[PDB]
Image (cartoon, coloured by chain):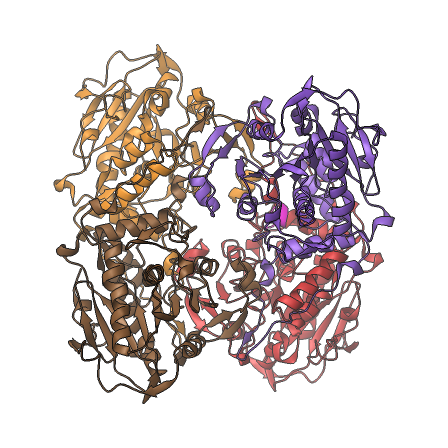
Chain colours: A purple, B red, C brown, D orange
Amino acid sequence: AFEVGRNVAVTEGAVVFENEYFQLLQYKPLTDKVHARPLLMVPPCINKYYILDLQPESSLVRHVVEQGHTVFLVSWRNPDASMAGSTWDDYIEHAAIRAIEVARDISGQDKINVLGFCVGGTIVSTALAVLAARGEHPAASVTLLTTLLDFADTGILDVFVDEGHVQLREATLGGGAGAPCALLRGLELANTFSFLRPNDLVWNYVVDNYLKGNTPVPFDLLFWNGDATNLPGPWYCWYLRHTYLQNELKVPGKLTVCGVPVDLASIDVPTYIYGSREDHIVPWTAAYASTALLANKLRFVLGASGHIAGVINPPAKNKRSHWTNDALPESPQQWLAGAIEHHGSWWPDWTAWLAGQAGAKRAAPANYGNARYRAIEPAPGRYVKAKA
Amino acid sequence: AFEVGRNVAVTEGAVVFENEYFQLLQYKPLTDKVHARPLLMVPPCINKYYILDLQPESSLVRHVVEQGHTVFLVSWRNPDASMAGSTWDDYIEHAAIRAIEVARDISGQDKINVLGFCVGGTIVSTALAVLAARGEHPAASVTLLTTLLDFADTGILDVFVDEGHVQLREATLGGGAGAPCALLRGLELANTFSFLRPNDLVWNYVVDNYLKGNTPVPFDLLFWNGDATNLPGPWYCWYLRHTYLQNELKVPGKLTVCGVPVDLASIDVPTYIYGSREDHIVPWTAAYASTALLANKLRFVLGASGHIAGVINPPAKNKRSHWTNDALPESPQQWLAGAIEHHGSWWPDWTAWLAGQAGAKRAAPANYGNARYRAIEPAPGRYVKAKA
Amino acid sequence: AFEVGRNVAVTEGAVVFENEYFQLLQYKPLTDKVHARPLLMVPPCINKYYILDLQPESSLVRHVVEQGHTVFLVSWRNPDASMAGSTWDDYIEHAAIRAIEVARDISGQDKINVLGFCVGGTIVSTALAVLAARGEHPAASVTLLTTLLDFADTGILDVFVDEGHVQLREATLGGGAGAPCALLRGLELANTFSFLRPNDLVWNYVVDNYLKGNTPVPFDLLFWNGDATNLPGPWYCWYLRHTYLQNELKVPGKLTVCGVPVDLASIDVPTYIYGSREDHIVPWTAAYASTALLANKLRFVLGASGHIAGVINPPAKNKRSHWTNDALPESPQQWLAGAIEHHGSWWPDWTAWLAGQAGAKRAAPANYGNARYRAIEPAPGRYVKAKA
Amino acid sequence: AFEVGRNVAVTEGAVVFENEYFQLLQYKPLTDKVHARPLLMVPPCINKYYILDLQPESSLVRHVVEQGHTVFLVSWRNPDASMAGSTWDDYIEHAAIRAIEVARDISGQDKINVLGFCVGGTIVSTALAVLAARGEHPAASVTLLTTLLDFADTGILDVFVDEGHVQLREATLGGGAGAPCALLRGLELANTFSFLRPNDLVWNYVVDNYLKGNTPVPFDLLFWNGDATNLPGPWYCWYLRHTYLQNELKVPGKLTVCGVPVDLASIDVPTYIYGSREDHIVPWTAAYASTALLANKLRFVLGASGHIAGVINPPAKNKRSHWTNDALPESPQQWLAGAIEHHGSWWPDWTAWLAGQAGAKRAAPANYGNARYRAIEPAPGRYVKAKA
């Protein structure tokens, strides 16, 4: 039976910082030397971080640590009633930008590597764009795994498109500015698989039972997906309105966040973009659309299989395949037509790229954090253990 | 501002029967003569019946009444805490089969015409199959508007299909019988547009605001769609499990309902099947799949436009078009390739077909119901006014 | 029985110019006054021009003439053995650019309006971009009906995408420059409906017979589609290679044509872009992609129905509908979500826009052409009568 | 450089029978013992048989021979001017039924195993249905690799569906019986990849060059695909009309072939059905539709990848994966939802199934054929060497 901290999320480490929003974990080195620049991972806040450190055999964290990188990770607070009014901006400032600042401080480096996964990627991208408009450039590189930046054709609009009346007269839309997200208060249950689907006792019961008895969806995934998290009402409103519905984050300067316009092209650092071919949560062609929005040197890699199966594919198992193509045409079909299929995991491709941005190796740290930020408790930390 | 009984659902009539489950409405004639056989309409219980009698200009009820048919309609109870354990079977027996029995009794006819809309169609079809296995045949004809019988490719499965591990060994599924629907208790909020989507304060707020300001979705539709209904937990479990997930109602004899196996081919009466081309709630090709399951003489008609716009298209407005094809090949694309597009509403095509199954005209009734079932209160009735 | 010049392509006019490549037609006015700026129409060279002047009731030419515009039209030569080496560039220089020069000369105007249909649109766009790199700006406005500029996802690539080997090693593509189009010589039969499909005696026989007996595809369309044209081998090679396969015309400066790089954004004039919703030859979302490539004020309109049915929809018949939306988001689904459906033909919307770019009305000309270019023979001309 | 009989199609064997239509090859055993029942392979006549014996490393023939089965194979004649009037029936009687009779005669067995690939599968299925209506049952089992029986949604219809006029009146289709296939005479070039696409000098030149320089489509595939075959005009007409266009072979009794109605359910033998997931020539869901038409015990297996890459995946290379599911629901998506992904080639799954239908092992034959049918020349034979 799965248990966080006993047989799931067991990579050794410590919490080195915490605030209302999150706990920053730092993992124990597993090598004698490590790269100068550490990697900060920003996982999604829809479901918990541990999908990235699921079990020892399948852990991305462990794998990266074993390649000689110092890893820091944002373990999100499962929000309580005091955070029922927390906003998208609050998370960007007090968690994403904060985590970057703390990791950079502990590392002693001018620049760190950053990774985002799913909504984590959208969060980290936004945070870095906010930072760039402030004239700050704390990232050497960005890795976006299964991240949506351009939300075109995610399908939430579809059932409404053919409901308009046939007009015999000049007609105009309503055109109003929406009721502000700040007028809501609440905690709404969320999970990854059913994020755009019902979340109610009956649906959760019927679906969970059907999957277990009629499909080979793995138990570890069902465990993680079932360990729900609460989303603050204004946060959830903002995300739904400005990405899925209005698709504005990809329009340079359209949105204002934490006092500045968000222009994704302003992040401007080497960026590794990943998608999974059979992913219906983040269509691979939607992840690919990030290539049209970001500056600097980009690499796109496509992994075989599903949303979780494609991303969590450790090389030791020698399973699946991935595709690479150095050229980045506008159209994903054109990208694929030119791509070469390679056996196995895409992890080695990424860690090779990451090594290139991480500087020279030096002796590994013996302790966690620094004088300012000392160890608080062992990873995985108590925040990840909180029920929604 | 919309108000049920003041400017919506105003076709004149009376409640002639009521029980815990529903109120049966009977409409006042608008012609001197009417067909011998009346039509009973079974609307969906997801949202309220009035989408079928929306406003005088757009009312299907009014239109049918004006063609000389006596119309009875099932106005569903918005379930309360006493009905938090009501089942799919309870609804079939105590509402659908009951409504048929009461309408037949009042009419004095051996057979009546029946119409189902959306989930109403699935309900009425099930009820009639149950009746046929009991050796009872109360319907002269069936009309299925925007009804799913075969739920293949409705897409709820999609995000889970590519999550299985790659096996190097013989492997088998879990294969268990599911936890019974009867173990749940509850009332879950439901609406048509978001039935397979979230239903929560934030989603409802964000979506409603976005539609109003950025799309031409009509206000009358948004009113109806926003007037939610509660679904009993076991009912909701059954529907989700046996149709959308396991797609078993279309497998003859697979499901047992109200003590008998359900075989759709056992309904065996002339049947008019309708779908709307741009409908993403009930794909037209899914409605078309009913043609492969039902016996007797079938007609399929395809209306232009969306889920509501295509079905609620009164002929007076002279808008849109529909397609007809007497041949019924297995494949819907083959059906369409041979179909002729006709100007305007499909309503006249249907009412012409309906006239053919409804017998000879005779003088209209002066009063509602009969000695056994007298008028209780005026339509639209108090049940439809209850908030969820 | 259809016959070009007897009951098809009968709008009154004259050939005022001819060369190896085409005949320029000028139509007789049907109004006392006409706009200062005439419209030159460049139809496709795949099949013949007359789809635009099909029959009096269905003629776009006649309709535009009746709104008070002087219309000139390019009637393409059905190439003979002497033209088996004609190139894409030859057509741009000797036909498209030539037609513009002759129409401008006859009109006496500094600028003319231009329309392209299907491949005609791709041709005229290219010609105008070539002209703009030469510093010439002969067009006041451009109308692109059912035109592909960005050829992404037209599907010719699809059957080849999943044929690569799985590599266990670093691998690279072949990467070679293609064998030049100029090495081919030939005349290849072409038609619109089967342009990406077989064109052989058996296919043409089987398809034509099946359509006539099992579908409502109209006889006038089948006549036009069956009246094939020959494509010079190098022309056909260029078109297939640089648009459908490599999709390079949309990459600013990528292609060199008639000595200059082609940059579509350099046309820079008000542009009206049209697509038909159920068009599978030119997907409406592909026509919509033109909005991302062109400068100046753009309007996009979407007509209901098929490739020919949607475009050839004269207002007198009062059939179908079209959609308008002044906003031009990047994604076509977002455009549609905000669009208002309007009854009937889109023609009046376009001719209203066209009136705005065509200047003041003045008395209609009494004669064809001018001293330099006098009438040669009556429209439709002998070129359009030549068999392939 | 590829050459048939030198480094392609080199599995050792002999031609043991020939007629105007084909040469029957028999392969030399590579084991001391072989199953009692041999396997006859019927490859497509669109392109040549050798895709099934491509190179020693990638040969399906060699692999099956190495598992202990006697293999016979139909090597089709590349038709000449004398065969420009050959019909679908001629091929069924004089090649498919003939090959079965000759293989059965040489083997001395009451029943043989049969395999069809692509159009070969459609041919062999038809032949066996013809045989069953004659009361003959020469097959112990059937293997259908990448075979279309139900041709629904292959897309040839699509561009014509939305061209009908809007009718304000009762309207009817043309409804005529088609001009007979027997009125055509000719030899039409065909290849697998472009079977539903142009086949002309320019297309073949442009596509071949583009694939070589911009994609990883393998050279061996391009060689095979480029080695075209001629199709007799009536044969081609029949195939196109009755499968792709009218989809009649799947309607029991609809078509008459070689004097008898064709009912696929009459074949009635254990059948192994295979499809490739990313195949756009034979969609895997179209191959899956065979499960609804055939009697007896069926197995469906889905291989990963493309049309050729998925089927030609030898186990030694240890690449890709395949899916299995013993249950056969009507819907392919439901089949997939329950399927288990297995590492590597599907070949071992099939040869294990085939062993089960092939009887007891006995000593391998020392010679080819029998007294009636002796060796004529060495495999691959001269027929396969003929240019179109």
Q: Residue furthest right?
A: A82
Residue D129 visible in rendering: no
**Residue B73 part of the magenta segment:** no
Q: How many numbered dots are placed on residues in this image?
A: 0
**Residue B246 part of the magenta segment:** yes
Residue C337 visible in rendering: yes
D46 and B116: which is toward the camera: D46
Question: Which residues are drawn in magenta?
Answer: B244-249
* Residue A64 percent coordinates (x, y): 65, 26
* Residue B291 percent coordinates (x, y): 50, 57
Q: Quadrant of the C terminus of chain B?
A: bottom right
Q: Is residue B23 left or right of residue D219?
A: right
Q: Quadrant of the N terminus of chain B?
A: bottom right
* Residue B49 percent coordinates (x, y): 69, 68
Question: Main SS of the magenta segment?
Answer: loop
Q: Is residue B360 left or right of residue A385?
A: left
* Residue D349 percent coordinates (x, y): 47, 25
D209 and A254: which is toward the camera: A254
B159 and C266: which is toward the camera: C266
